[PDB]
Length: 303
Ligand code: SF4
Image (cartoon, rainbow, N blue to C red; front, side):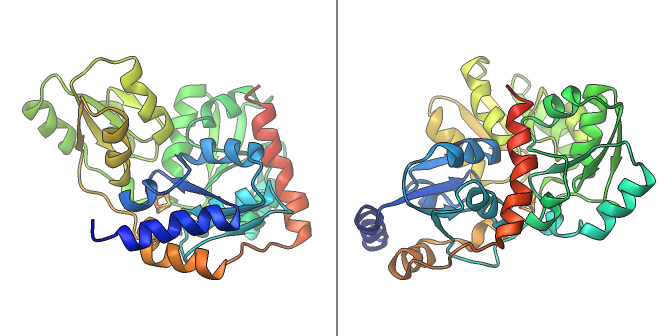
């Protein structure tokens, strides 16, 4: 195979330098295939609390890399492309959070993991799409401030029956903005398929699906549902992961959806990352000290 040169040197350097490679489900297939651990944000977070390796090569977006570093302040965490980021996460600011706390002083601030680390210092608790409902449901308040994703926050309100005040205005992920007409069409084409969509999808898409969950939840659905075909309403990288786990099922994208930021990581720049041991994820000590609190609380409110 024409990529063997890069694959081989990645595997040699990883072993030589004492790295573990962690990847998100939306990384390109070639990188998922060289990673030691591939999963969703919640799975990556739990892995980050548990791993023993002194050095971590993280393959995803910056807020995830930073969470891994917050949970491992004394380990070296590197990323191939320091600009890989989540634009949705980036629209929420400290300024907005403080405005809404004042406006709603007894509402806890619940931040989606897709948020800047500075913003996380201001949060009462963090959540991911897999545990957002459980986390908010276990809080002792009928109103919560939630951001940055309006769709997830609305989904939380539905499932919990609580009032969810979303910040900022119109926070959403462009990648998950499917039209519900694509489900209609796919029902005609594959009448016995099961439709699985992300909670970041708009309400009409969520409401027409058979299942709604994080990518980690998506991967467990075929363990209990015997359907021959699943239609997947998330970023394209998940198709590879699903097909690999369940080669006897068919996985069909709801629509082709690509996260440009998740695609910034390549075999070539991942090799360079191992060769140079760059770019290190560095945070102020204060940010780590402060952002760790709502991350650890997330885990307390699961069990
Ligand atoms: S798929 Fe959407 S929410 Fe996820 S990292 Fe990309 S832009 Fe952010």
